[PDB]
Image (cartoon, rainbow, N blue to C red):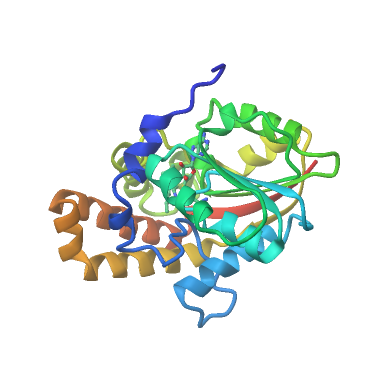
Length: 285
Ligand SMILES: Nc1ncnc2c1ncn2[C@@H]1O[C@H](CSCC[C@H](N)C(=O)O)[C@@H](O)[C@H]1O
Ligand SMILES: CCCCCCCCCCCCCCCC[N+](C)(C)C
């Protein structure tokens, strides 16, 4: 109400078709950087490793209520429930993800409380014990960053903790100063992504996040980069989508197929050269 969630911008991507995303994401449908804890893990094992890495920093205890901001297709929520025995609330602006997670909730045999809402954090006003947000922060926009942290710090308990996992990047007009190549290919890359893949998307800077967090009552006790892991994650995603080209075009179109391949491979290369990063910020209240 005070802040209208950007449903259209987010749904433009995530509500394309579950069957389409199923063509390149691992079984859990985790759509974020995996963690190859061991160099020989499969994409699936690596995604669970990333979920445990994030959830393991929140000091979870049975009965707690965990808030997942930008729950995607629900893998993180359901593992928090099954593995850590905490109640959960997931927020998403995607209709298909909400509907999908609602089915996981309907068929769950676990006794804990699980809720999924087709709503943004902008509309969530319930006290929670801990918060986890992986890959959603990039959709908030520069004009919501402060509002987001203020809300998170408010809803959390006295000794609350939020694990914010988000992509971060260097400004093109800075990579050029240090004498690094392809500063133009990078700027052009970012434009393509924000206009054809993630409308309204914004690339956060580590200093930016650090600033908004501290300025809102949080103490970032740790920053962990998984940069190299994303290049790998993206290469596995593009490898899968390519072998599924036929199903991709059939379910969608050659236009969508070609566009997503450019997106996936392009991102992988930008992580490979290190112009974009991904970090988990442990935010202590
Ligand atoms: N303002 C907002 N409030 C709630 N969810 C939001 C949001 N802006 C973006 N999101 C959600 O953030 C997610 C980005 S995709 C990441 C999904 C999941 N966390 C995973 O790691 O697999 C989507 O589910 C999108 O709907
Ligand atoms: C894998 C995505 C890499 C994006 C690199 C930088 C380009 C644009 C700036 C970011 C804005 C949108 C980010 C959306 C991230 C979505 N996922 C969590 C689903 C990957």
